[PDB]
Each structure stands twice: as structure tokens, then as C-alpha cells.
Length: 225
Length: 225
Ligand SMILES: CCCC[C@@]12CCC(=O)C(Br)=C1c1ccc(O)cc1C2
Ligand SMILES: CCCC[C@@]12CCC(=O)C(Br)=C1c1ccc(O)cc1C2
Image 1 (cartoon, rainbow over the protein chains, first blue to last red):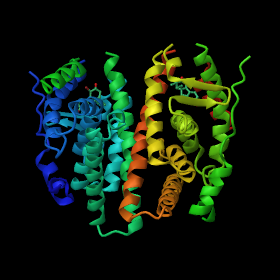
Image 2 (cartoon, protein in one colour):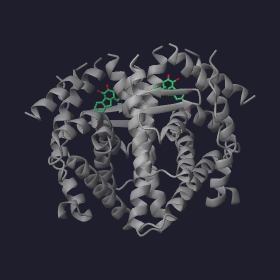
Image 3 (tube, rainbow over the protein chains, first blue to last red):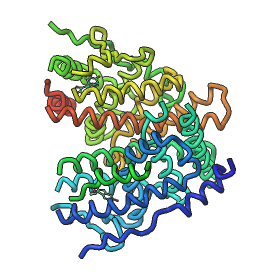
Image 4 (tube, rainbow over the protein chains, first blue to last red):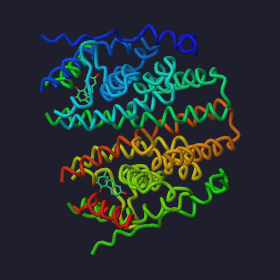
């Protein structure tokens, strides 16, 4: 109830944000990168557990959602981290990248998908409160199977609340009702792009390094046991 | 101007809908399927040329948009065609499929992504006017590169108009302002799913039949010359 209310929901999400992850280095890009994800994934699962109502869904649903959405959530965080640095990607404190470093490959393709989309978010002037709500939407909207009898009723309620909070945030800008709808529409259309980049990253990842998708699956098990 | 107005824009789109395509048969599924797309693509390009303002964009933009969005537009049409037939996919008049025919493979995965998403549109009670506006959004939102000096100003104007028409359509249902936003949000979140299915179909398609993506590219050239 209360916890799912716009002002509160948004401040609960703020405290649930994952920490800075240091890669901690003593196929090097891809070595750096896969070790990073392994690290980031642990925190991702913690983050999800702090989203009001998520742990009360079915574990059959929790596991489905985290499995399908991990790369879009790590990419959404990445764009938010690089949003002010045109030309770069800020993967972590000691791991920043130039586009011309994405020349050594296949990675260059993905690199430009993430710079472009990020530039789009810059132009829209993505607010923190907006960022927090969209990343939560990405997790809850990541699959359709899990919302095809109570956990479903629950999943929708919890997804509708987040959409309510975003709408709320936007209404506070003091813009016109038409601007509101145009902004809500521009924001959610951008998720289609996010998913695209995710699909490509996932693709690149099987054509190959650390067992990110393995261990995660493993983390998913312990998460159940 | 006028042509981009909600009631009119929606009736212009109605007359621009492609015809019934008969496959016309005298790797058979995939033979049927690739021949079908070759056929459907010709009409797709005609359809796009009837969307007010599209031919006045740069050809550098026209070609980018059709190239990136062809499979999502053929899948969006497919779901609309099967929306009332649970368990099937209605690819064309003489080409209907059962899920258990999608067992002979890899195609089964995709098959369930398209049944699920379609079921979602059923539950939402997707209206014709709504269908017409979303399919146009899919084409105009298909890439971000082309909207990263006039053709861009133009592209946004033309995408904003379509979003205006959809919003208009939804406001006519006589539902509550909160229902409006929740419905607009539910509709555009579904595009993320559409793109997902597209990405998978595209994937399946290179791992392989008719040169769909070749000839299309070819059609793209003639389209310029
Ligand atoms: C353009 C290269 C992007 C690498 C990105 C996608 C490709 C990949 O294999 C990995 Br493991 C990647 C990754 C790790 C952590 C993170 O937060 C985001 C990503 C995306
Ligand atoms: C589940 C199988 C789907 C086949 C679908 C995606 C896989 C594929 O190779 C082809 Br050519 C396909 C196709 C053709 C026409 C059309 O309107 C839609 C599609 C999607």
C-alpha cells in the first residue's frame, strides 16, 4: 500500500541503488567486462529484493524476471552513469572506455547503440526520479510469460504502481497535459531501444571470458534454496 | 498539418493497409515463410509511402527506418491477424499454423513469443484504430541513429503526431485520466516485446530459404533510384 505510493516508492528505490563496483584487476576487455557483470549481478539481486512486493511474488516469477532482464538493467545503469560523458562509457570507477577502444571487436556495434540511446536520455533531460522508475519497469516488464493466480494479480499491481509513480513524477514538472503524455510516450518508447542493445549484448556473449550467465543461474538457485 | 490530425491521420492509415498476401505454393515451412516475407516486403514499402510526411524525410532516413523495422512490422501484422485465434498463427490465407507444427525447430521458441504477446493484446482489447497507430509508431521508432538537420526535425514531428493520435483514440473510450495513462503505458511497454521477437526472428534467419534480407536491400536501392 503505502510503500507503493509515489513519493515513498521513489525514496525506497533511492536507498536500494547498488554500490560502485570496482572491477579490481591485478579478451582482456571481455575479461574485465565479464568479471564486472558477475560482481554487478550479486548486487542486482539484492536491489530487486528491496522493491516493495517483489519477494512476495512467486519464486517461479522472481527467477523468470531476473533471468530475462539482467543485461538491460546493467545497461540502463551504464547509460545513467555515462549520461554526462559524451564519447565515453563509464562501466565502473577504474573502467572507462573511449569509442576508439571499442575497435579491438563486434563490440563496436554495441558500443554505438549505447552511446546513441544515452545521448537520447541526455536530450530528454532524464531526472533521477525518472531513472529510478524506468529501471524498475524494465525489471517488472522483462517477461510476458510470468504475467500470462495470485502472483500474476500481484505482478500487475506492482507494475501499475511503478507506472503511477513515473506519471506522478512527470506531472510535477509543471508541464502541460499534452507535454506529460508526450514525455511518458517518449520515455517508454526508449525501452524498445534498451531491449535491442540487450539482445545484441546477449548475442555477442554466447558467441564466445567469465561464465556470467552460468553463475547467475547458479545465484538464482541459491536465491531459491 | 491536416493530414497529421487525429481523425484524419487514422483514416489515412486505414486505407494504406496492405492486402492479403497469398503465398502461392505449387525447410518447407522456412521455404513458405521466406517467400511470404519477400512478397509482404513489397507491400510494406508502399504502405510506408502512404504515411503522411514519410516520403518528405531524407532518403537516408527512409532507408534506415525500413531496414531496421521490417520484421517487427510483419510480426505486428501477424499478431493482429491471429488475435482471435488462440493456439494458431495466421500467416496468410493458405498458411495457418498450430503450435505443434512448430515442433519440426528453434522456431518453437519464437512461436511461443508470438502467441504470448498476441494473447496480451487480446486481453487489452486492442482496437483497430489502436492497432493502426502502434504499427506506425513501430516504423518511426525503429532506429535512433536517424533522429540523433531538417529530416530530424521532421521525423520527430511525425512521430509526435502519431503519439497524439493514439492518445486521442484512447481518450475517446470515455475512461478516467488515470486509465488513459495506464493504457498508454501498457500499450507502449508491449513494443519492447515486439522488438524482442523481431531480434530472435532476425537471429534465426541469419543462422540459415529465400534471400529475404538481400532482395529487400535490393528493393531499398530501386526505392532510391
Ligand atoms: C559495448 C560493450 C558492452 C559490454 C556488455 C555487453 C557485452 C558483454 O559481453 C558484457 Br559482459 C557487457 C557488460 C558487462 C557489464 C555491464 O554493466 C554492461 C555490459 C554490456
Ligand atoms: C515462429 C515462426 C515465425 C517466422 C518469422 C520469423 C522467422 C523467419 O525466418 C520468418 Br522469414 C518469419 C516470418 C515471415 C513472414 C511474417 O509475416 C512473419 C514471420 C516471422
